[PDB]
Amino acid sequence: PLMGGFGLKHPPPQILIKNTPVPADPPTTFSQAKLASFITQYSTGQVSVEIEWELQKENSKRWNPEIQYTSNYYKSTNVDFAVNTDGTYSEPRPIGTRYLTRNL
Amino acid sequence: ADGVGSSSGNWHCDSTWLGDRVITTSTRTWALPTYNNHLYKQISNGTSGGSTNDNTYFGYSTPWGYFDFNRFHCHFSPRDWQRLINNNWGFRPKRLNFKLFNIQVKEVTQNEGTKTIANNLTSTIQVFTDSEYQLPYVLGSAHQGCLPPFPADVFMIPQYGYLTLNNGSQAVGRSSFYCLEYFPSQMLRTGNNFEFSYQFEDVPFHSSYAHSQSLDRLMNPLIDQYLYYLSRTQSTGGTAGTQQLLFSQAGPNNMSAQAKNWLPGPCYRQQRVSTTLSQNNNSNFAWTGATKYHLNGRDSLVNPGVAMATHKDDEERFFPSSGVLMFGKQGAGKDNVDYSSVMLTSEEEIKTTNPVATEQYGVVADNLQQQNAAPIVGAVNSQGALPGMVWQNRDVYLQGPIWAKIPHTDGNFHPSPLMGGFGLKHPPPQILIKNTPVPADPPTTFSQAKLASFITQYSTGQVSVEIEWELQKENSKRWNPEIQYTSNYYKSTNVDFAVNTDGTYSEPRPIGTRYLTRNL
Amino acid sequence: YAHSQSLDRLMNPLIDQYLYYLSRTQSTGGTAGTQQLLFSQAGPNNMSAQAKNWLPGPCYRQQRVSTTLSQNNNSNFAWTGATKYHLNGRDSLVNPGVAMATHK
């Protein structure tokens, strides 16, 4: 994929969910028209997704230290990757996946 | 175990195509109201009012509703119907399975002007099938109220009623009254579900195909016949007309004169109507010039009638008045709607074996000729069954009825439904459903009168019907390509057999079942 | 046994049919009679116009005779007006004939 990712011929199936329609009271005389009146309704619940990942461990003879991803040492008004005073979670920066080096 | 917090069933819609079987299955959401305030009622219409003698009836409307799946588009998507009619010569139903599940019962109450709706967890509904066919069988009259063609629609369940012998509006002595509470029925609360299985009796395959040969062309075009016919009764080329009997062998030159083993199917004539308005007469002949039958003093229109070709070659515009099934387009009125709204079916394919609906069956002699008396030949407008006669049944449609119940009688002739379908002596039992009445608070002092005050109530739920179909595969040595049913290639504002911008599912045209050919 | 339903009344009296029939060939209410094709669904109001799956049994007509003497014609039509069949040059009276209702 050009956005980056894992191209999959059979990706994880997409899960579809819908509230079953519940009709409001029909008339007492028969009518062929479909029922256009429903009870206003919504649903809530919990969802768990669990992915097992396989890792390729870094094995390298490089003598000097690697570059690592580290948080800023200096003081700040609020912590990065944490809620603010109002309770809003924010992500300060995009975090790329490549800090390690290999030989080309 | 069942309960108020667990679902009684799952949603299933599929068509499984395996070998020579196809199993179609549908699920819909229904809503069943309370009919007749839980009352049986006599209903009748007499000739005393503006009604004529033909329209009189006597019968009863019940509190009960009933499920009707009897139309094909209940069980087939337009794509599943296309696989069927393109690839197969015939099909017949084998068995069905039926389920009610996920039943909600809800009470509704009015306070001033506000409405409110609440679950009633302890209420029931009553469901029974008439396995023994002890009730008037009201399916197969092509009534509305079938499951919708499109699975996302929610439909109202139709009220059950029946008609009985009458004289005028009054009832005769043989008139029957049926109390439906007098059968055993299963009672279901919101955790209960209902199921039964039915197996179709052996029925001939509906023939989905056209003949690639007309009935009168079965001959070899190359070879003469050894039989003779009477070619000429008069002397040819002579200065006198002296009569002489001359015989000839029929051959490629005159095929119309050859001897033939078979005859076209039976004929009962219809009046011809043109879609071009100028060609029709100026009058209202719809009822007057109609083809009717007369039963116990009441004239009943013959609709659609015996299966007959809609029109002959190179006449598109003519159709028999009552002869063809007529379907309406989505959102069409019930009364005096214009021609553009209806969809006229046509039988093209049976021109081979069947006479044209609007024309005479043939011509027979009216007299015994003499040297004095000229021969006279009359037309045959209506012709019953003769030996050596072959015909095709009317074609089923995606919008049309699947089966009918063969009346129980001493005798019948070729018991196949005239709307098209599968005639069944033991059709699928009709399923009856009703909300059990729940009384409003009775008085604190005893009274003998029955309780007329009830809690306003209705129920909803899910219904699954699953039919296994047997297929007759097409095996043909035809070299050139068949005609197939195909969607239009050109662009359009909206897709055929799909919802529009407003969400309304529509069916553009009736789809007949015969695109394949066989040899006659 | 007798049937408790006539052959043409097998319908549900409550519900309309989804099929249509040709109700009127002429323009209604207009100062001109210009022909126009108008279709309608048959229903409880007109049952005679509904589509039906079956037809009444076969018919071979008989001459009608009244027990009231005054109503009958004055002649002897017993043999002459009789319903006969013709077999090898001999006319045989059709008796009793195909099963048909005696009277309406």
Image (spheres, coloured by chain):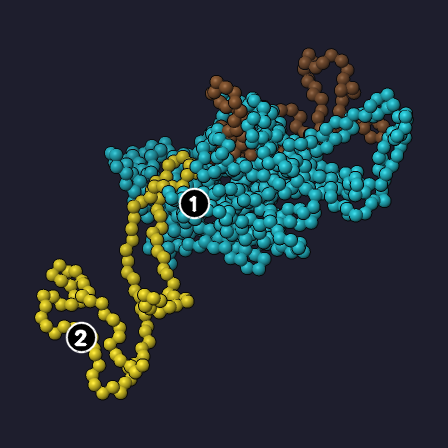
Query: How far across and how far down the image is residue B147, in percent?
Result: 46, 44
Chain of residue at mark 2: A
Q: The N terminus of chain B appears in which quarter of the rendering? A: bottom left
Which residue appears at 39% of the width and 54% of the height? B8
Query: How far across and how far down the image is residue B512, in percent?
Result: 56, 44
Colour of the chain lettered B: cyan
Does residue B467 appear left or right of residue B11 in this picture? Answer: right
SS for tag 1? loop
Query: How far across and how far down the image is residue B391, in percent?
Result: 68, 41
Residue nearest the observer in this picture, A99 or A35: A99
Residue nearest the observer in this picture, B131 or B312: B312
Residue holding disc 1? B494
Which residue appears at 29% of the width and 34% of the height? B443
CA distance for labels 1 and 2: 56 Å
Residue holding disc 2? A70
SS for tag 2? loop
Chain of residue at mark 1: B
The answer to whether mark 1 and mark 2 are in CB contact below 8 A is: no
Does residue B359 appear left or right of residue B317 in this picture? Answer: right
Chain in brown (letter): C
Chain in yellow (letter): A
Instruction: Report whether residue B53 is seen.
Output: no
Instruction: Report whether residue B351 is seen.
Output: yes
Of the residues shown, which amino acid type is indicated by label 1?
Asn
Of the residues shown, which amino acid type is indicated by label 2?
Thr
Q: Which mark is residue A30?
A: none
Which residue appears at 77% of the width and 15% of the height? C76
